[PDB]
Length: 245
Ligand SMILES: O=C(O)CCCCCC(=O)O
Image 1 (cartoon, rainbow, N blue to C red):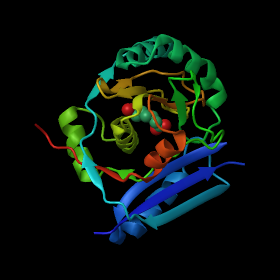
Image 2 (cartoon, rainbow, N blue to C red; image 1 turned 180 degrees about the vertical axis):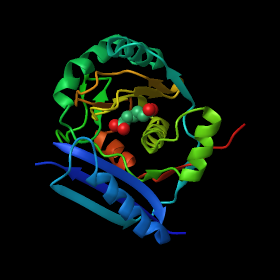
Image 3 (spheres, rainbow, N blue to C red; image 1 turned 90 degrees about the horizontal axis):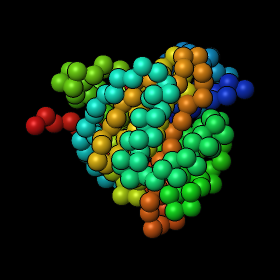
């Protein structure tokens, strides 16, 4: 009944891969191996550095539902991004703060973690630079997740499970207005915008095949210092359990 946070990072020289898991002890070997195997064979390359790490969690665990999901079919990245910018505005980010974020996204391609963007300053809020803010201690039991996929008619890919767990944890934070995300994997072009009102909005094309610039940005409207928020994001333990209605 004690849970452990289990984290993996892998890189070349370029970031490669990562994983966050939240598990009971008896699943340690299976989890550590799954994270290992995940790091070794990624399409961004085989890594020359990897770290795997576990710690007992002392905070109590909150179980939540996943964000509601809707999938937007688009014909091209440019259409995808336009729709994304529209949905961020719909969720409450001002056009002008959106534009400033997009001016910076190319420079964030190297950040190994999430970027926090303050809607009050129109500027990046966190001071982690290339490290990025790390969202952790969230997970989604597979069996529950596969039932969710079957009902939702969405493919039971672990990377959707991971992304929707992160997005659901993150959107629950009262200071987070929206998240904008697409992959750094050259072979996966689907991304999303996520928010409290629109839920998890998948957008089937957010970049071209073969490009490696991805993005993850949280738009922050809060009254607290950024370190508090960084601490919430790292420390609040979250499990996703879906229940049909
Ligand atoms: O909703 C999806 O299809 C998952 C998109 C998230 C991509 C993040 C990644 O795997 O790099």
